[PDB]
Length: 300
Length: 330
Image (tube, rainbow over all chains, first blue to last red; front, top):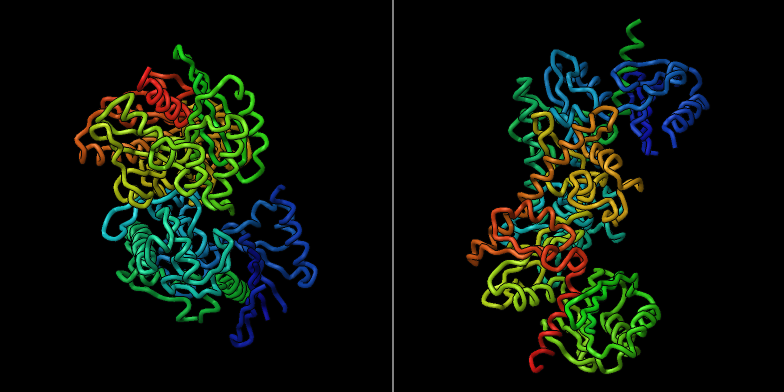
């Protein structure tokens, strides 16, 4: 009975014992990964809090795909902060495909990480990944819509759009049914509802208009056209990485799987939600570090 | 002395235009969503010397939770308590109407930030040209044909016809200019987070002065070039420990190119449609506009009337339009 703990909200995966697993949103071994005013205070809080009900049997998955024991993370806290893709990438390279591209999209960013010969070959820092099509700052929920493009086709004409914070990808996702209303968990830009109509109201403000000047069908069309711009952003980046590493297989996961599938039809797609369930797909890092800890402790 | 008063949502601009042509522009903080006592007080200092007043309200303030009637009524009452019936209100249609006419037809009082300026240009500057006014947030590209302003009616229609562009000198989030930028020779994706704005680019490239970076900084830090480069570096999820000052300035220069191109393309489209080669520029962003529209025949409000007028054109414009009507029979 080993647990996979991803503190960012927090997700827990109960692994081991023939394979009996389950995840929950908020034990002999615990894999601790943190994807979440100096950033050394919270680090101690997390570490010390972990010791409380888990003891010393805690393995921390650092910035790299390396598992460091406790106290090692207490000494040099500059390794505790980990990405939301490193753990998943490691897991994929040893349990799904050794030659592929992992594409994960959360509420804010999309990670496109090449895996070659079983090893993760993505660049290190965020800057380096932005420079190599391995980090795309578009997410399922929090992306301001004009980041997808400052012009949009509206009623057949290329139209300029507002730069003000009015609508986000969450609005597009709900209107196009790529995520449920319940999955629109971030704050709405105007402090109002997450239902479709409320989302259409927000989207209409992008064109300095409202649902009195334009119809709901017109507004929905704005969402549809932005969705295609969004798909292209995902596709172009994955293609660039694929062209350099010769990979054709893509493993997708995260809240944005539906969007990922739509954008990457040109590739051989392997869905985490389809192979391990939607729960794992929504809590991949926690499940990943759980499987990884198992194999490493089984190395004995 | 003629007074041109432009009441915005939070800031009021007053132009004192003297008979000899000398002028002075005053600035006053006056939130329209609250009581009008301060406005009334300031306007009263002109009560016994001024009888010719041009008043315009350009307040947009999107959702201010206040009816148009109360907003207009409060402004008109503050002005009336100082000048009585001696007030000419510039309405949305670009015409001067009486104080009583404004009260009655309150729904037609509030004007766009460019309405007065465009009409003034059409009368006092050039009858066939394109007005390009870039303030802190938007860029208005308004065609003037045969002395008549012929821009589209609504903002949506202007967005569909290259007459409204959401790029400004200070408040534009940098990624709105483009979600990728050339860096060290390769196409680089950029953050969507609110970390840097056009004000940062403007200060770093000296298109505006540090004192002119009047909006809040994204991180609440300094408005100096160093602090601006720090914010700009965040757009590529970096910092001045990972990249250099030269690197950060290169990010700013590359974005400046995208920014100028956005302005140019929009102005070119309006110009090609009307066949005009003359552009009249104004607003805090004149330095950027001069660079972007270098190939056009440029007429600068700042050069012809001074920096203050360029940064408060609406108030000056209605003062001039009032002067025109007055001189009509002098």
